[PDB]
Length: 268
Length: 269
Ligand SMILES: O=C(c1c(F)cccc1F)N1CCCC1
Ligand SMILES: O=C(c1c(F)cccc1F)N1CCCC1
Ligand SMILES: O=C(c1c(F)cccc1F)N1CCCC1
Ligand SMILES: O=C(c1c(F)cccc1F)N1CCCC1
Image (cartoon, rainbow over all chains, first blue to last red; front, side, top):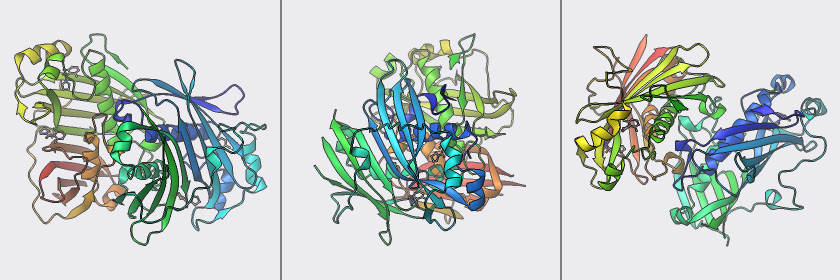
């Protein structure tokens, strides 16, 4: 991978691996999400930011401040097949004192056509107290020189799927997958659960008949709380309708919410 | 990746990814195992085999026969760091009518030194009845032209740790991780649990203090029964021992039917 000619975005090519594909011989949404996360790491390394998923500066490290994902939105038109090369382009943009946004464009290396796109909202948080805070001007100026100055949105449409309010699922849920625990392969280098695992856990409550006859087109996921290594999760789904679903991840014991989201599927 | 000059082995280079590393900022043993599996797929594709992990010929497809892993053995000297390029070389060899063997050599692309090695035993099985069978001569002659004729072993040693008999763990186990279920990310393109998942499940019963102070040097794993998508697994570990050795057992949570048995060796960091 490498920064583009203007140094305001990053591109990387990936060959789809054998263990990265689902039952339709194409990459899973979790493989796509892992690749967006990997290209985001390489963009942060290529410009001197901390490489560990938190994209910190020496100022943030001193203050014990990290960037955390608050929302992930992904739309896939064509899943790359096993052996195919996918080219992902990523860039960041400041959203004032609210936080940062990271966008992605997925393309077929052979045809050059857009096969998918993603957007994510990141917030500043103290790693110890887990207390969110507004972005300070000392921090803003450190990353602004690596962002395009004019708006560059992967999802430009005025009021679109990526910025909608997600409601809380009402009990009883139509579908559920209970007793979900993370293993060591689900943890990152800092022993925290990888944000791609939450996507897999959300999709675990989608019935197999939907997976066998439909393809996932859109997924929006809000991150409210983190799941610890020794926590147990319950995944809940209800049909709100193409097939649309409302999702909810909550701790198995007290029922504390960790995630909420929506998925949209198309008939194959 | 590509077949070597003689067409009797395959090489491929991989860059270690950010989500592929553990707490030490180096590749996990499951990432290594996934890469050996990927280079094995590409070797099978480069010479005309099925590619779905079963390495089948038109003869094997007609008879509903597949190749399945019976044993996996891995020894790692240095785990590649995040960003490092690892070069893996793989080849196959016939073991008479017992089955096939697939071997691997892991090297650092910059230094050219051997950082790891693996060996695996594969058996012929009917897809439907799940009944093992000896390798027929019609099948042998279809893959023998893609194998070295003289023996080429990743583990040559006269007395080596890849061919030892593994005993069955006695209850009560010293350690255990109970209620392990596979999710959709644990399944392959044919909806079966990926062989690498069993390795992760075995390591789940190893206490965190061992993982934090030791590095995994050797892992031997026997595959006895497959875990279905809706099965639940219990992982059991007991210390058999500067080095730490463990005896492992994977069994179904209900009836206690054995699915895997193995051994791990760890050295102090
Ligand atoms: O400060 C950055 C960042 C950037 F603004 C440009 C390039 C690389 C970076 F890590 N980020 C905040 C969270 C999302 C990424
Ligand atoms: O505490 C978290 C969080 C995390 F810090 C890591 C993983 C998942 C999480 F929900 N958040 C609150 C603000 C949005 C993210
Ligand atoms: O028949 C093969 C094979 C081979 F013998 C040479 C090259 C590629 C192959 F898939 N195998 C069966 C078990 C796994 C390897
Ligand atoms: O029943 C299995 C098996 C399988 F066929 C697929 C996956 C895991 C398994 F333990 N075996 C019998 C001896 C060789 C492996």
